[PDB]
Amino acid sequence: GSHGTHAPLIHPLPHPIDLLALQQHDPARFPLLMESTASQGRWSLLLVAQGDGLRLDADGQVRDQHDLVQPGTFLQALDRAWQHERLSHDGSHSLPFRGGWALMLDYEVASQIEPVLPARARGDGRPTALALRCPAAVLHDHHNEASFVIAEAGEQALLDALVALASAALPEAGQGWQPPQAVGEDAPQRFTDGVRRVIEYLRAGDVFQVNLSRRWNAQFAAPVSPQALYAQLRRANPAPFAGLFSAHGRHVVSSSPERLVSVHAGHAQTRPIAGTRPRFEGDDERAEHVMLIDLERNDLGRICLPGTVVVDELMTVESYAHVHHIVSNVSGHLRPEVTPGEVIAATFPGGTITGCPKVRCMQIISELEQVPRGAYTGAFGWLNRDGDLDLNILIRTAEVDGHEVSFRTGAGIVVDSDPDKELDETRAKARGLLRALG
Ligand SMILES: [Mg+2]
């Protein structure tokens, strides 16, 4: 009666390897790189693709590697592909990724989740979202010099070919960085008028906080290298977590992410990896303290077992003479047949970079920003065959397209916000990135 286990193959490697270089070498083979700090020190992970997967295309349809239209939304198709290769959980997590899919989702996935929101294709016509079958990974402990290949049981060949083609060169990545030759941004009036319009909704009492953003761009003389950009940004800000996703012409460099959702053996968690929820204040003696709970919020609470959900402070808003403590469900145990798409649907996009209440804030964001957010406040990361998943919210994140780098920054508007100050805060957030582009 004892359950068959499916431990992943794990081969220790000759010597430390350069994952960035390795990706730069064969981007097609290595669609996603992620860096982390254990509670140890630094490490990295590079996912190895095998060539199947799914994409949500600009015509609003999902397709696979054979360009066949899969019916439904990206998250339905993703759920069918996961069921098809689903594994049962073996209860061990030394190793956080064990094979399954690299995921990248733009913010605009949200209109498939809440179809009240107008759908938007990417301007460049590339895929809004991707799920890439990845049956192996390369890991690199920074603390201990150790590198490994890991692959799903039954992938001995692929594992072999990777042990081959690691320790084979190391041309050495992310060199030839050229600073940009022009820099640009949305006309500032668009933002400050957006803020004034946000403040009408806040004064009406229908929303309590809204993350309003604006787009920045940098133009270069020669085509940009995603890994060279990545290296610039990591040097300039060595944040604990980061990554780089690249495939299908999407090139998404993340320099300061937050956790969107983590699931380990059905235990789902949304708490900031930082450890501390965000505080939002405007530009205004004993403050009032009101706890606010959105009773219709669609979140982990809808997909978890009763008696397991933990509630905690999502964010605070502090204006005039009050502090509102915005509380939501932050972790729980999933019902046993909850699918990865349903966890994504319950959690995406995060509440602190849209607003509260979430859906109404997304409609205001959509009307005021007028263009897709792309990777900004989207997510990427991975899904294991056993359903474990790790997705990050993309906050300090740039996209590369040929000679152009773009990125958005935003400010959490609250009822006593000052429009020109919020504008300054968006520029203060862009400064760090623009510095590093130098
Ligand atoms: Mg104040």
Image: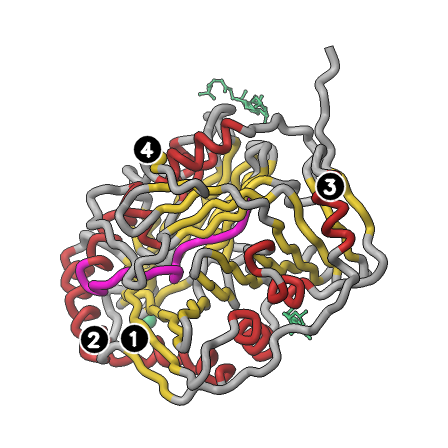
Task: Look at the numbered discs 1 and 2 and tell me whether their residues touch, using CB distance below 8 Å.
Answer: yes
- Mark 1 or mark 4, which has the lower sequence index? 4
Quickly name the residue at label 4: 71
Q: Is residue 292 above or below residue 346?
A: below
Quickly name the residue at label 3: 157
Q: Secondary structure at mark 4?
A: loop
Residue 334 percent location from the top left of the image: 50, 30
Per the rendered image, the range of residues in magenta is 367-382
Residue depth check, mark 2 versus mark 4: number of the one nearer the observer: 4
Quickly name the residue at label 1: 422
Q: Residue drawn at (77%, 54%), measured in percent from left and top?
A: 164
**How far is the residue under mark 1 from the one under mark 2?**
8 Å
Q: Amino acid at mark 1?
A: Glu
- Mark 3 or mark 2, which has the lower sequence index? 3
Q: Dividing the picture into quarters, in which one does residue 389 lie?
A: top right
**How far is the residue under mark 3 from the one under mark 2?**
57 Å
Quickly name the residue at label 2: 192
Q: Secondary structure at mark 2?
A: helix
Residue density around tag 2, few if under 14, some if 14–19, many if 20 or more, within 10 Å: some
